[PDB]
Length: 330
Ligand SMILES: Cc1nc2ccc(-c3cc(N)nc(N)c3)nc2n1CCOc1ccccc1
Ligand SMILES: [Cl-]
Ligand SMILES: [Cl-]
Image (cartoon, rainbow, N blue to C red):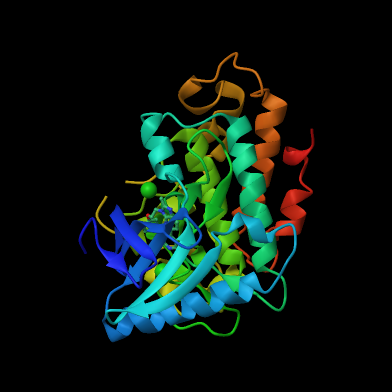
């Protein structure tokens, strides 16, 4: 697609903004609205078109709901078919939270900026949980959270290409590996709670600069999670189709790890407080004496993250109750 093309006496293509398995995203001048827009151009392959039609349906469903929470998700302006490609037109946004970490040389941002991100992210999750929506994103990661403006800390969620409503699930293998919830690793039916799991993983990474759980495979992934949060509850592993991919049951109805060729820190011993550096002056001690990073501030953040990383998705912290947490009290 050329960097001067004109479409439908309406759009002038400027540049490639983004690429994907879905196709590509281009910067285009909308001659009617007289503004720049982002156009998501889907490949003319049955598979991407079908999944993108679902994304359009979910996006248009959200547009029909006027609240104070709807403006944390990229607004879909419109869509059309051109040259046999489904085209989604969005408001222009800026760079993503991963690029923001890259720009800190992976040293992380302040707890204060982390809090501002958490609050927006939790308000978006609350909006998707409105019963008549009930949309699971299924691919929350730093790369799918964009700054509205390179000067500001306003963010919006993008990419509803993996998203499904509750009880419209298609795939068992969903979510980006590092952000994949245990329920989805364990091959169990997933909720809106898998996004809260992902959000917890992201918020830590935003502050430390490194992914909380960077598995090289599903097995590696679950082992890195168990290092921090210990063995999942028996009641969960008993109902889990793929419990025996990672764990083994014992005479007395208790569970342990399947082992292979040696090494990980033993279950629950890689403590989040050390990962966060609560009482050691933040991540790698780099925040020693910096304001808004009091041990009290860090402990509230630690408490909220462990509510987002509950193994049980039925007791894992839902969004309204994450906005009530002391970590957000000024
Ligand atoms: C700069 C900019 N404005 C945007 C507005 C919307 C979207 C946008 C992108 C996608 N995949 N899905 C939706 N629903 C909206 N992406 C924008 N980008 C950067 C584009 O890069 C990407 C590419 C792939 C994934 C994420 C960001
Ligand atoms: Cl990443
Ligand atoms: Cl996915």
